[PDB]
Every structure is written in structure tokens, then in C-alpha cells.
Image: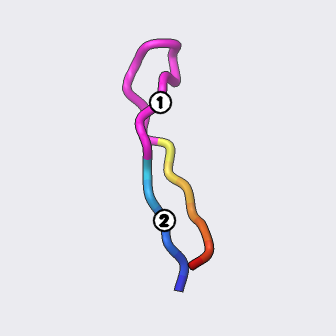
Amino acid sequence: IKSCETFIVACDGGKACREVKCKTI
């Protein structure tokens, strides 16, 4: 099984973004 999660980053230099990512367990 693989794990995945999203984080909050400045996609517009100062906005709310939901960039999802996956990694091995």
C-alpha cells in the first residue's frame, strides 16, 4: 500500500493551494 497526503503552499505567491503527494510506506 502507498501513502498520500496534501499540503498548503503559496501557489499564487500568497494563496491557498492543495498540492497532493504520494510516498512509499
Q: Which residue is drawn at 53% across and 86% down?
A: 1
Q: What stretch is highlighted in magenta?
A: 7-18
Q: Which residue is drawn at 49% across and 72% down?
A: 3
Q: Residue at x 60, y 67 (%)?
A: 23
For residue 22, the mark is none
To which residue does mark 1 refer? 9
Q: Residues within 10 Å of mark 2 (few under 14, many from 20)?
A: few
Q: Which residue lies furthest to the front in this view?
A: 25
In the image, taking residue 23 as reference, residue 12 lies left or right, namely left
For residue 4, the mark is 2
**Secondary structure under badge 2?**
strand
Q: In which quarter of the image is the C terminus?
A: bottom right
Q: What residue type is labelled 2?
A: Cys
> Does residue 7 sit above or below 25 in this rendering?
above
Q: What residue type is labelled 1?
A: Val
The secondary structure that dominates the magenta segment is loop
Percent from the top left, x then y, of residue 10? 48, 22
Q: How far apart are marks 2 and 1 (CA)?
A: 16 Å
